[PDB]
Length: 348
Length: 4
Ligand SMILES: O=C(O)CNC(=O)C(=O)O
Ligand SMILES: [Cl-]
Ligand code: NI
Ligand SMILES: [Zn+2]
Image (cartoon, rainbow over all chains, first blue to last red; front, side):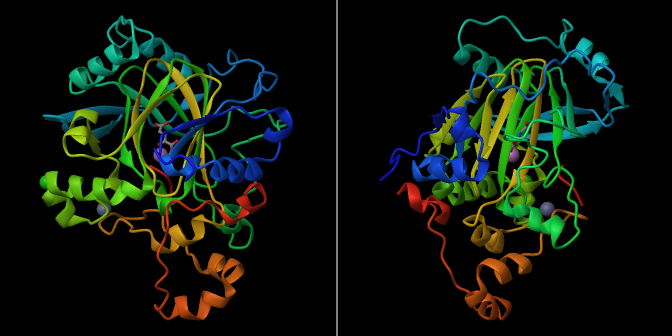
């Protein structure tokens, strides 16, 4: 098959390939990129989303989060504390500060070792979930603010705006700030652009193994699992690569550098950390292939106002011949995680 | 409802 090793792939589009976003996503799926659950896309050298990052010092981070982490033997739970609002300027000064700055290191493996060794000490501040875009109005290629995929149907046909899902979010990171193991809301795709600063490292589990990771997590955290089946959607659970390896969960790792895109795929579990002060922009998107994942997604029961997207409009428009069955609860379709989105047909 |  295409990428039978399910290893994270990197792509280097020309400007002409880069211009149509949905089409290029269909292309990288025709190359098997989706099997890893994560892919890197390096934009053309000529392309920039913004001329300068030195005029954003006045941007407000309304709800910075201090990340407290408790655990041992590769298994941790992360607790957020909302701090008072601060500007990018203040944040940047705390991030580049000596008590929170990146430690000295040679190779990525050393930094990774220090991350997993020091995870629970000196809790950092994450500049997370900031509504906004650092793109300039005029940039029409891979603009995270408007990607023009079928996810837009939630807005255009239904008038529903879900912040960070069909709208962009900014993330100002510092060393050791983390994102816990999760798939996207409604098992959507996500896109992530690192605007500037130090790298972001990522771990990914192939969608075809996602259930193995869930059973693993349920084993380690039975109480959490008993309270909510989808408790990983709480984005509190950290699990080291050593534990993944010990229990035989296939995974891959990759480091994203400023100027690079990461794409996560439906039901791709991923987690990671920031190397130092940086800024990333992201949102969710969809393709036709997502619709079945959306229909099957297991959602958090226990919490108030979690993201729940009505699938009705999608089934109605793109699967009319299955709509009656689906409404009746009789749609028994089984997802094959290896298959590319239909749109890939012309490349295959 | 939003992302968190
Ligand atoms: O940037 C972060 O903190 C984590 N990003 C994601 O999980 C994503 O883009 O899908
Ligand atoms: Cl537990
Ligand atoms: Ni994510
Ligand atoms: Zn829950």
